Image (cartoon, rainbow, N blue to C red):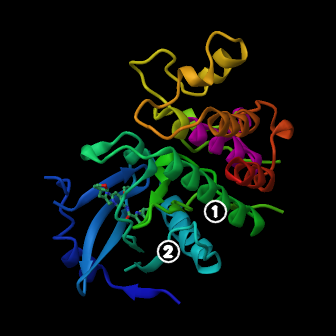
């Protein structure tokens, strides 16, 4: 149901894969498994991800993740998942519907001078991201790479989960290859366990990013890891209000504490003490009801 592109088409519509940033070219972002380029096809802006080995990955591994991206999106179409338009397999490329407002990570940092997200917008983003994770877990998929860089924002700032190349079927199993972003990863995931409970923990880190506006890791910050503020709040050194993003004017204490409560539950170090995604979904819905 996708569209088969040949590599020469995508090379042409990305200005020969111009590596200069758009603020300068065609490069919009980068990850461990490839670079995302802006493309223009028949007067339509698209996002083209050309896969590349940037994290010491083999050819078979990259191809396997390429096939997993297509498999997941072939069967999973949802309001809060990115929409694939096609691919190229003759270099591997994935062509997506363009997300004009980029990643949640970039909007939380106000990259390129974009205005700060309101608390109202952040609540809808948190709810939409949870709905996307729920849809994946409902379809027996573990995402394994949940982070704010992988939550994209469309023309209505609707949250769209992306990057399913590491996804695995779910019905507690183990792997020798530990993958993911450390600052978002549950302890058991860092140990090699594969479980949907690790997605919940990662989503908790995203919720802390949404509340505070701070990146999950910042080497020039104390604490360096954002998840460490939970310990500070529990040990009563500070409060969640001490860390609320000051770049909002519409955040109220009750709903902010409501989303922190969800985040705190998601961030239980013991995996069986975490809520499932469905409970996270209902807690976030009660936050705004
Ligand atoms: C990796 C960063 O990706 C983007 C960055 C970015 N920056 C802008 C412009 C800024 C300037 C002002 O605010 C927005 C759009 N945009 C779209 C981006 N991605 C997509 O459209 C997109 C869509 C589906 C999948 C994927 C991915 F999985 F491959 N990516």
Give the camera-side residue of 272 and 15.
272
Q: Is residue 198 magenta?
A: yes
Residue stretch rendered in magenta on the structure: 187-208
Image coordinates of residue 67 in percent, x first then y, are: 55, 72
Residue at the limit of the structure toward the top, as seen here: 237
In the image, residue 270 above or below residue 86: above
Image coordinates of residue 155 in percent, x first then y, are: 39, 67
Image coordinates of residue 140 in percent, x first then y, are: 76, 65
Q: Is residue 244 magenta?
A: no
Category of crowding for the residue at label 1, using alpha-carbon neighbours closer than 10 angstroms: few (below 14), some (14–19), many (at least 20): many
Find disc 2 in the rendering and name its residue.
83
Say which element carries label 2.
Answer: loop
Residue 138 figure quarter: bottom right
Label pair 2/1, CB-CB below 8 angstroms: no
Q: Magenta: predominant secondary structure element?
A: helix
Residue drawn at (54%, 20%) of the image: 242
Q: Is residue 210 left or right of residue 153?
A: right
Say which element carries label 1.
Answer: helix
Residue 97 figure quarter: bottom left
Q: Is mark 2 within 8 Å of ligand 1?
A: yes
Q: Is residue 69 left or right of residue 246?
A: right
Find disc 1 in the rendering and name its residue.
132
């Amino acid at each position: 149901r996708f569209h088969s592109f040949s590599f020469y088409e995508l090379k042409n519509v990305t200005n020969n894969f111009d590596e200069r940033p758009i603020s300068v070219g065609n490069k919009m972002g980068e990850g461990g498994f490839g670079v995302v380029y802006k493309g223009y096809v028949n007067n339509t802006t698209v996002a083209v991800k050309k896969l590349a080995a940037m994290v010491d990955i083999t050819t078979e591994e990259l191809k396997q993740q390429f096939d997993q991206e297509i498999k997941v999106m072939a069967k999973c179409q949802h309001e809060n998942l990115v929409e694939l338009l096609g691919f190229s397999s003759d270099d591997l490329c994935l062509v997506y519907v363009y997300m004009p407002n980029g990643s949640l990570l970039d909007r939380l940092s106000c990259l390129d001078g974009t205005p700060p997200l309101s608390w109202h917008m952040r609540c809808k983003i948190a709810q939409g991201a949870a709905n996307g994770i729920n849809f994946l877990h409902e379809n027996h998929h573990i995402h394994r790479d949940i982070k704010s860089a992988n939550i994209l924002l469309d023309e209505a700032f609707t949250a769209k989960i992306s990057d399913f190349g590491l996804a695995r079927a779910s019905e507690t199993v183990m792997t020798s290859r530990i993958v993911g972003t450390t600052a978002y990863m549950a302890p058991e995931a860092l140990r090699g366990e594969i479980t949907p409970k690790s997605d919940i923990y990662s989503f908790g880190v995203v919720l802390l990013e949404i509340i505070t506006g701070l990146p999950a890791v910042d080497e020039h910050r104390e604490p360096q890891l954002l998840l460490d503020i939970k310990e500070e709040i529990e040990d009563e050194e500070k409060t969640i209000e001490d860390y609320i993003d000051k770049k909002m004017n519409d955040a109220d204490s009750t709903s902010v504490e409501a989303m922190y409560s969800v985040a705190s539950q998601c961030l239980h170090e013991k995996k069986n003490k975490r809520p499932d995604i469905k409970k996270v979904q209902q807690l976030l819905q009660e936050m705004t009801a």
